[PDB]
Amino acid sequence: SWEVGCGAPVPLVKCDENSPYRTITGDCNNRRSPALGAANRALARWLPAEYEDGLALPFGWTQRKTRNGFRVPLAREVSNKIVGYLDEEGVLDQNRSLLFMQWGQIVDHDLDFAPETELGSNEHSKTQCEEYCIQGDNCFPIMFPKNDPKLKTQGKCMPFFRAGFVCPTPPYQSLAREQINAVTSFLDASLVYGSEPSLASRLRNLSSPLGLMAVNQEAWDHGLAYLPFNNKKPSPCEFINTTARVPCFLAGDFRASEQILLATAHTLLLREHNRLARELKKLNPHWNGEKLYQEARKILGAFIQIITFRDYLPIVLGSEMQKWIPPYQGYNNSVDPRISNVFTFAFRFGHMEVPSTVSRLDENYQPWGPEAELPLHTLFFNTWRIIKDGGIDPLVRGLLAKKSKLMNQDKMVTSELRNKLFQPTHKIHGFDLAAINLQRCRDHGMPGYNSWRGFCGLSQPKTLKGLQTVLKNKILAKKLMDLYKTPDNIDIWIGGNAEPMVERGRVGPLLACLLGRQFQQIRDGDRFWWENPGVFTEKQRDSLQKVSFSRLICDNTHITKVPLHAFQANNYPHDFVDCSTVDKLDLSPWASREN
Ligand code: HEM
Ligand SMILES: *[C@@H]1O[C@H](CO)[C@@H](O[C@@H]2O[C@H](CO)[C@@H](O)[C@H](O)[C@H]2NC(C)=O)[C@H](O)[C@H]1NC(C)=O
Ligand SMILES: *[C@@H]1O[C@H](CO)[C@@H](O[C@@H]2O[C@H](CO)[C@@H](O)[C@H](O)[C@H]2NC(C)=O)[C@H](O)[C@H]1NC(C)=O
Ligand SMILES: *[C@@H]1O[C@H](CO)[C@@H](O)[C@H](O)[C@H]1NC(C)=O
Ligand SMILES: *[C@@H]1O[C@H](CO)[C@@H](O)[C@H](O)[C@H]1NC(C)=O
Ligand SMILES: [Ca+2]
Ligand SMILES: [Zn+2]
Image (cartoon, rainbow, N blue to C red; front, side):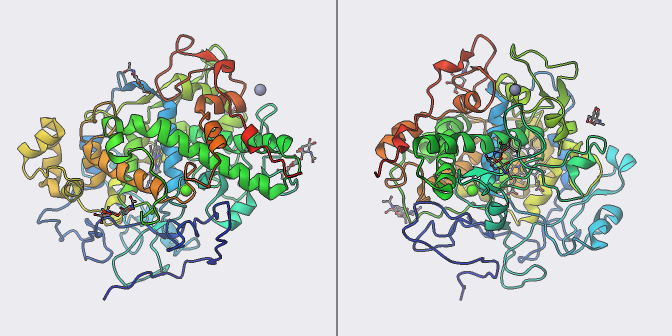
């Protein structure tokens, strides 16, 4: 009956069995199934897609089509009634730095991107969505509810375009619509190096055989480097300040400029790559460009994997870490390494950890100038504030010394993202990321909240009283029930995010299960997992073991005061130490002596 593999959007299947290095595309990781976890393939389906017409149309598409006998609520109405709040006082996470937020976003961009469709980059269909708020084909606009303030100042809707799907660019009736993952499923620094050979070659410094990445030849972080500019026009980063006219950066990932701390994180990974490569070269003068690009790329991939699994995941998953991600037992070629469709929503727990302001700090970690603290919404697609307002060092001090927002059932997403989000082509700081998330859940054919509770062996509330006990919140349960009518219909993003956090974690039981399963799979299903025998030497792993975000800052900035534990909330100078006391990455176990 069922086939195995639709697809024209394959590049070239050209696997070197003897290769010590990853492909850029993620092909050839699994020997038995070589396209497994490759980029530009369908997101994995842990559960069958749920569409209004069983094939492709989202729930909420046809006004007269219920879900389980109830109209699905407007995404923007759920956002206004449940996700929004006014008072930023007391919202900050008393034991997570802002870098905890920022690393989450970095790891997400390494693992998944479902890009919006393109059957019109030169069309009236392009602007007919924003202009006329007309639903059709890939235009699935987020309509405003009657009492919405934006109805008064912004028109009838927020334009929204359906995510791209695998096989055919326009129509496809082969089976259910499957959304694409444009990046590699492996935790492999694809966001630094790219997931397509072309982008991957557009980015490298070939002009020297030192295996360095291409840099900005127009601005430097006072003796450091900038990501090159995407000189492609029109530029959203130019458009936010036509005076400054500073373009977006060019990274392995097209999202790198979305906000200034993401652009900052990415800058450090371009720079850290050079610091490793040059260290490699001074130690192995005989090695050519490739061995230094490929080998440098392999240590950085290993760095991300370690920071993610050693430092990041244990303070997300808390008491649930050991349950879902037990100590590593080695590579299992039967594990599916593909990112699931649901994971791309689960991992959006990060939107509730984003605070309303970003700060630039000085060597005493004190306000940097008179406009040191800036509203987050002024920093979307903002590269001019890095280049013309003192490079990345002051932002990096903020990442260390400021705190993440804490998820709060009564203060979910800051209005900087819920009302003032900036998106390219669109001209306003007027988008709602929460509403977008809910619309996207439906766009992607997501099973509802109880399908996912069932998937994770958790109770399935069917009444108001049921929902109250699971959320441990009467008022929140009552608002969701008024909007959704049955818990079966709660969109996974808001359902999962609404659950009280697990002991010593930052997500509830459902998300702990979904995130935990996915992370276990991307480690165990990865033939190039840093700690898989034959990837690194027993001695390198003693030394790759040394790596730190604390150390990565010290070694690629002019910052000399850092916490040891950079994801915990750190207050200067009390919880801060001098850089000298921080275990460095001894690359002596990479020393090559052939002759
Ligand atoms: C200021 C910070 C951030 C901004 C401005 C931002 C913005 C966005 C936007 C605009 C989208 C696309 C929404 C859509 O069209 O469906 C998105 C998706 C996403 N965000 Fe965020 N985000 C932020 C922080 C984070 C954090 C901290 C995390 C995780 C810890 C995260 C995880 C995700 C994930 C997984 C997706 C879906 C990616 C995909 O497969 O396409 N984001 N974000
Ligand atoms: C690739 O690397 C070379 C060598 O590291 C870069 O050229 C150096 O950088 C600046 C010019 O921007 C000069 O002051 C140095 O003296 C240059 N050295 C050499 C040996 O050329 C070059 O800019 C990089 N190329 C790109 C496109 O990023
Ligand atoms: C490699 O992973 C596979 C699949 O995740 C494991 O296969 C499981 O085997 C158990 C017990 O033998 C079976 O009951 C299940 O059918 C499989 N797992 C799942 C999730 O359904 C396999 O055991 C793993 N190999 C090793 C050595 O751990
Ligand atoms: C644009 O950038 C310039 C510096 O290049 C700055 O002085 C000015 O305040 C910026 N304007 C806006 C609206 O951001
Ligand atoms: C803060 O988080 C860390 C984990 O990084 C934990 O070990 C520590 O006990 C926490 N501190 C407080 C005060 O709860
Ligand atoms: Ca990747
Ligand atoms: Zn400097």
